[PDB]
Image: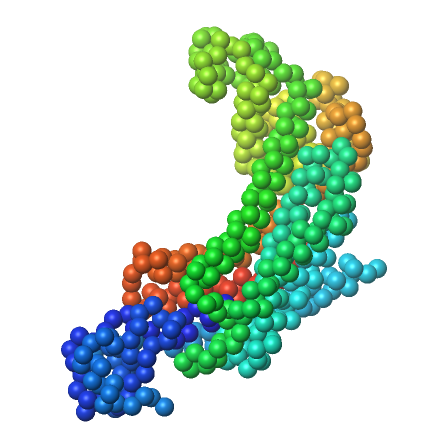
Length: 70
Length: 438
């Protein structure tokens, strides 16, 4: 209702330039349709979350190797 | 060195501390307050009819507030039916309240500008036109709240919002709300106020036209200074051309000492501003000026034009009774003054105006035509005072979406925290009506 409808989900304002190692990453999930910029959020084994562009070649490879977050 | 997403968790803890207190106070004040109004008004004045329409429209939204409090801090559990029900009541309250105030502005316009015979248009408006012009379009604007308002899952929790098929629907209802609920009622209230004060200032001009007298030529004062209109002094200078040039500068037009009734009124209004600004600066005249009506002020301004700021200030004995509202006791105590025997015809017209509070002491028409303006102007200004910090938040947030202001995650969440708290505080307009009785 009103304010809660404005910005309720995590969005990507920028993407990771340097490719990430598969050994440190645990899962992946895409950004909400509500977000201005599309992309995926890589969940590391460490716990921290990293943005990435879905159009990138190294990102498309990591999505194949990793599962979707539960 | 890693890129992180924009976490909205910093907005979640903000709402969980500040908003539960705000939604609790406004709920209790809006249910005890407006609850008593409907029981006292409806069961057992003209503007009181519109306040009955207002106290029922906001009360319907007060019983809707417990749902607003839970959605802002926790999650939406209530379901899809309550989701549409809350959205419809919110749409009704947004356009009904803002157009009831617009109809209040129209009621004051008819009661002040066309008071001669306005009992019929004022009745027709409050008894019939109010339903056709306020409640019928308000219930007709709830159609999208029956189509697009529904519950949806978003990341962490469920959200009850209006979901449109594409961005073209989002931007047309975005611009529709600004017109019907902010610009169009704003024009109606502004255009009423601007022609009510225009009438009020004209009534003083015709009042002093009778007393002092209108002169469309440059004439010499009792003291010998060059004057024009209703006692408007041009210069203390003994030169005619100096005053003639001073007149051309004040008007803008190259006049040869000749001015029109309209030009004479423009100069008059300028002299009233100077007299009012000086009166509210005087320690013995300022606590009296605010206590008086609209016609009783005109009679006090008349005394200032006749004697002066220093002269009127010498009525310390009479000004004390003038605040105590003992109008019959003050007039008999002011009739004994040397001012009354200095000029008897002008003084009797001014003292009977202070005694009764009627402009009919000069006008050859009706009697006891007194109307209140002070409770209205407060209610409308205090209404926009609640919404002003909320519409500031949307304006800044709009530039972020229009790609004019492009900053980080922190600034993006700062405007949200501003909107989230100013939305909760903007609902105080529900409590505004019963609190105005104090």
